[PDB]
Image (cartoon, rainbow, N blue to C red):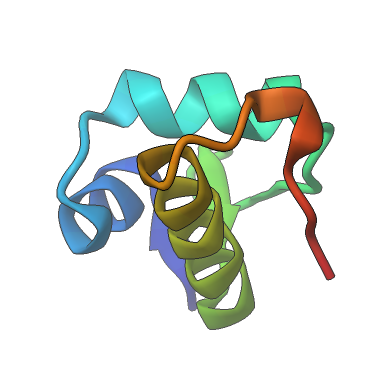
Length: 67
């Protein structure tokens, strides 16, 4: 009912491994879909877009602010 890692990566314009790096580094919650794969919601996409935006602006991973 939601979006897997490939879908998220597609909407962000990054690779799937990049999404996985951020999710784990930033201790972000991730569910599992009907196949047991990682799954994300629209909220997650927005949060990960904020991560990408902040890194792009020069913010270090540890200085990132998340809701």
